[PDB]
Image 1 (cartoon, rainbow, N blue to C red):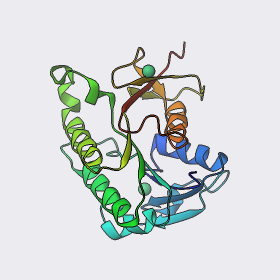
Image 2: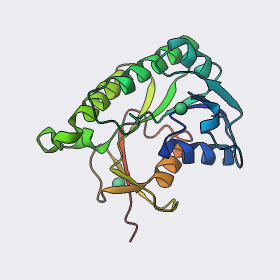
Image 3: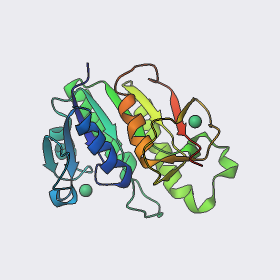
Image 4: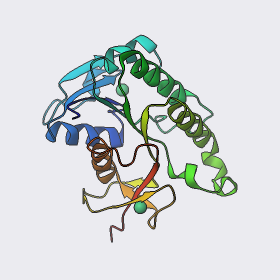
Length: 205
Ligand code: NA
Ligand code: NA
């Protein structure tokens, strides 16, 4: 089964709770971060910290080596400018997975990849363009890839009670960051979402 995982993006909002939940679940977790002090110094903490940059192939290789599976939660530090930082990070992650024979990757993009393109808000088009590039990298890799395409990510407490919609939009437009992290981890325990797009969502009121 899956026992050793790498998490990319662990210092972001969904990343931090995914990381805590992964450690609590008993995974042996490796993270790649720019600064180890961005991780909590108390509570559940990962087994291995690599300090480096997801845009550097060798730093990513050190992080993927020896893993059973990879979680990808890269973002743009809330910058909406045209960018390739997510897709280029994913390119490095896939390259290292291929070199080491790691097959399983669970990666977050956004529900806008399931929208009619004519309805994506223009202000979010540049970030969505790079999510599309990232999804292409992962789909073309031939790895076992679960495409997680969440709607708006909220701060509601963990429920574990959300809906998972396959290959289409789901009936709520929000998912808590805690439920999203919970779902990321669920995708490590099953192959049934491999090659599919998944949309987690929930009604919190
Ligand atoms: Na970081
Ligand atoms: Na759903």
